[PDB]
Structures are given as structure tokens and as C-alpha cells.
Length: 77
Image (cartoon, rainbow, N blue to C red):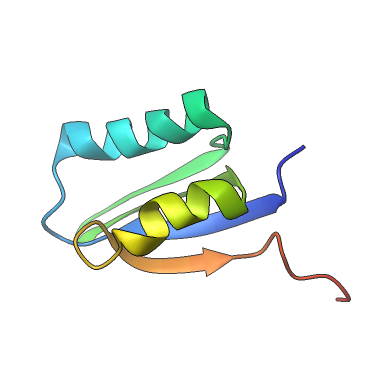
């Protein structure tokens, strides 16, 4: 149902529980998770998102999301 899959990342400040939270927030909210990124210095994840969830961590960005890459609202590939 989502608008597709997305890939967001969190700065190197965000907390651990926070990560699981934000992600969980999407799980409960709407978006889902299919994969995650537990790299050294890189804390991100990949899964299903939408335009709604975006605005969520889209505005608060900078102090939460380091990089956001939407692949749902692409159309015409």
C-alpha cells in the first residue's frame, strides 16, 4: 500500500533506542521496514515508506535524518 520503498539515514548523534523508535513509529504509523543498515558510522535503514511518514522525519530532518532518499514517488522509470 505504501508509496514505495525509501532509504533514510540518521546523523551520528541519534540514539540507539531512538533509531528503533523512529523505525517503530513508522511500523505502527504506516510505513514498514524490509532491511536495515547497521554500519560503523552509518545508521540507516531501507523499507517501505510514504509521503506522510516523510513529512514526519522530513521536517525534523537535520537533527534526526542525515540523508533522505525517496524511491516511492518516482513514477515513469
